[PDB]
Length: 294
Length: 294
Image (tube, rainbow over all chains, first blue to last red; front, side, top):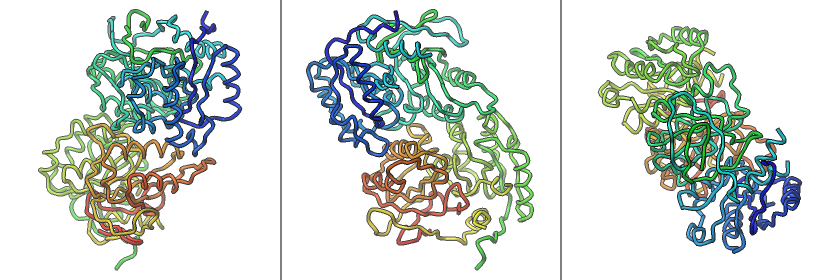
């Protein structure tokens, strides 16, 4: 059953590399982790505030590095996205991270920037809910939160997806992407999306008008070797007001996919809505039939 | 000497083009009537009334008009009708040889048009950062509109500024920049900001919360040789709601300018509000005390 958590072996490090956390949401999160018998390590600066950021870059880097020093940690679950984790990229000690025993980094939204950087450096990562999702359709939300422990245990290996137009084909490549806006906002920097040939690019977003989504897509595709992608795979675009625009969002995305001669898929249950099922970031997967399979 | 509301004659013909967002018919008509009141001979591009979603026609249609503005021998300025979104899309197909072959005809606009201003500067073509032409068809506003003809005629040479941070010594370099969001959105692409060493980077924006301004600022500065800039000079940040953020906008921009060790000025009367005085794009200027001069 998909609301059922798997035990998480070892300990989960909780860090806040992006936006600041409300006290009551943090405490509610920890209580839910305890319900589930999850042993955790709370980063020492998770309650820090520096404007809307969870502390200074230096504070956030200390917590992320500490998460990789402890030997019993088997996963690093980001508490909140929002904005700010790209700020850490010029400070990360990548060598200290490759040397630690495997511990997938987990989050979405802004955290997409760190997922991509981790993939570039050969580090484990999972695209899934941030941990404060625990402290906030309710059934879908609960299955999404449960999907993290289930993927860490290796017991889920597929999601449903639909091919939009085109023709029947099989696409195999690395799973990359996440939040369209966050990733576009790293183009031209050291944190630009890692996009090896043949990759399946997952795109999703929230609270944008369509012109801002097109502006970011144009930028993201112009900044990578787009013609060498295996596929573009849309998750959800939630709270994105159409405002009288003549073309649907899928028409716009379809025009871009056609321009680069890459197939377009959609309705992956991933994003900011109730459906945010975890998927392994940077692994080889196959688009076949009605699913994405790893 | 003349009042800032007093226009100068424009000789020859002004090409009106719409390389970004679509144009409302009534606003266009009022624009043309004001041009006629001021004795300005104009030519409308064949596709300026095109619509393709929110864009002023397809890429091919807009390229045809832009190219035509450089093919016609009697055109002495190319005044963009509206910004909004879309002119970066023209960069892959733009025939620079064809533009460079034509007699001098400054490109005028702001907002999204900043992207084209920068590309023109990279290709050694004159450009002016100022009101888009539809601003005519909608006392400080009138002075802003008059400033375009006055700058084409070469009679205005300075704008007021105020020092905000960093060293107080004279800065001399090329005037670059414009809208922060639009320029950040070209980072990592063939249309990235042309930012030669020593430049005075002008920044301005409208309708953004502070975290979005910071995300774009971080990307723009990380994507150029920021440390080699001469200065950052802020125009207006119009309708940018603070919403309880603990740090002021001046504090945030101060922190970034300090991090790259570049002096920071503000209160340039340039942007989306009433105060949008024209300045020469890509021209060498001097920033000293309470004035920017060229």
